[PDB]
Amino acid sequence: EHPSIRYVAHPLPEKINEAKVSIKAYLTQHERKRLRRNRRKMAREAREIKIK
RNA sequence: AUUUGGUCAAUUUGAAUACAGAGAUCAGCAGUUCCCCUGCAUAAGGAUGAACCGUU
């Protein structure tokens, strides 16, 4: 009686606090190139405007 | 045997003015892409050095 034979326990499964390591999203070479092209282009444009 | 291939435009007109029709040439530098070298940063990843003992 003091420990019941009848019941089956389903105790709370303790979830471990997994540290969210934000994933290093990489770039394709092409993507990188595009980025380089665009930022640089923008800079150039700015220079032109700020020199014209 | 004859003849067409033959109308300057433009402007001022209500034929005159025009007269063929209105930038060139030489030279820098930067950017764009790709490559190579060099220095720095960023990540990652090595390799290695340095006397001598440490911490409740």
Image (cartoon, rainbow, N blue to C red):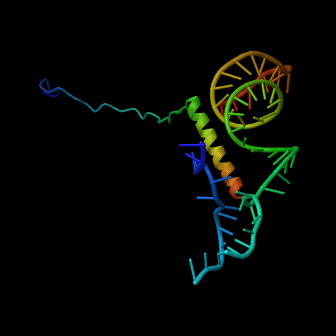
Q: Quadrant of residue B52?
A: top right
Residue toward you, A34 or A10: A34
Q: Quadrant of residue A35?
A: top right
Residue depicted at x 47% and y 35%: A19
Residue depicted at x 36% and y 33%: A15
Query: From this viewpoint, is residue A51 visible?
Result: no
- Above/below status of A14 relative to B6: above
Residue toward you, A16 or B7: B7
> Residue B6: x, y in percent?
63, 54
- Above/below status of A15 relative to B51: below
- Above/below status of B14 relative to B4: below
Residue toward you, A7 or A28: A28
Residue depicted at x 16% and y 28%: A2
Q: Quadrant of residue B27?
A: top right
> Residue B22: x, y in percent?
74, 61
Tell me the quarter of the image containing the N terminus of chain A: top left
Tell me the quarter of the image containing the C terminus of chain A: bottom right
